[PDB]
Image 1: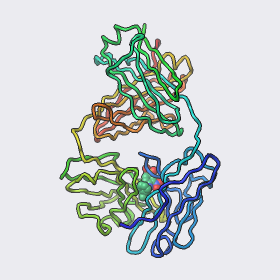
Image 2 (image 1 turned 60 degrees about the vertical axis):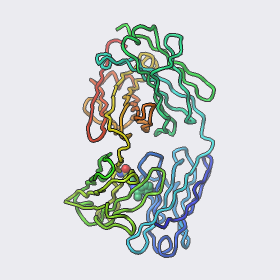
Image 3 (image 1 turned 180 degrees about the vertical axis):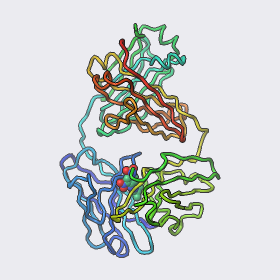
Length: 215
Length: 215
Ligand SMILES: C[C@H](CNNc1ccc(S(N)(=O)=O)cc1[N+](=O)[O-])c1ccccc1
């Protein structure tokens, strides 16, 4: 139950280098050339970025480089990009079929670019209307940082009920996505002239409006 | 994933769960080099099985590993709260290369199971007139909070332009997420349909939409 030692955190702006260290003992990190490094985005499977102390697998940029000096392994990430913001784990085989893991280093990429959300409002789908439902979805994507507020309107009035908004999650483009959904009945949908989704990000507001279709 | 694991497995306190890890004759079926790792999310993983069946010091005998042909299995018997985690399998191959499974989210049920409500929205008029044909597949009201989403163009898997949000717990204590497929109007208009397949607790639901003559 013995952890390799890693600093809990480390940070750099885009284009900077960060080095993170992985301290063992002579019977693990010092005792052989079996040091691995893993990159993991929160809620994602890890990726192997270094094995055998220094070797990069296919598809890992030469920006990632691994080294070892006595009982300490080091990973250097040069030319920091948004995608490098993640948890980094080291591991070493020891004696006795043991695999040791470090506690993980959270690498923060400081000063990532602010981005306003792309907002798309979807009226109810023909299929859910046939199933006596008229849920609307407001898709909020491509935003940074990962905090928004949503209000809905029925015609010009605030909608106080039937609103859910998902916790924004970081997507493959390193920007946040969330959905807000309004669970209306077909009657509520058809009785109003429009519904609107208002999205606030960094004190800037985007509203979209949909209306019962004429098709 | 190079090795195939089920995305999810579940049971209540005291139940058993068996999770599979399938490869080829040249990795899983080729030698006794299957390892299992347990990760509590945002914490260091832990080796819990090596050489198919071997438990590291201080891993309890609730955990057993076996292998038949090209499929290894981890059994966790008498599930306790702390067994709630992601489980990864690995196997060496021919080049003494190391192969990884996709990971299995094992939930110890803290509430009743609930199948997702899935709604597939075709492109809105506003986004179409702005030369985007993003589809959104809304997935709500599910427990456990683990889901996998595949998209089809006609009957062909599509990988590019798929984004799925990390399931978040909503006000009714159940999970919600959305997958969005960022099509171009040409992609959308030139195919007979697109489908969203949602897998939860080993059961899959499909929704299909096709272009219309009016939005
Ligand atoms: C020891 C494991 C590592 N697992 N590795 C792994 C798992 C899944 C995938 S896959 N098939 O692409 O989904 C790929 C890999 N990989 O190494 O490339 C661990 C380390 C750190 C934190 C958590 C877990």
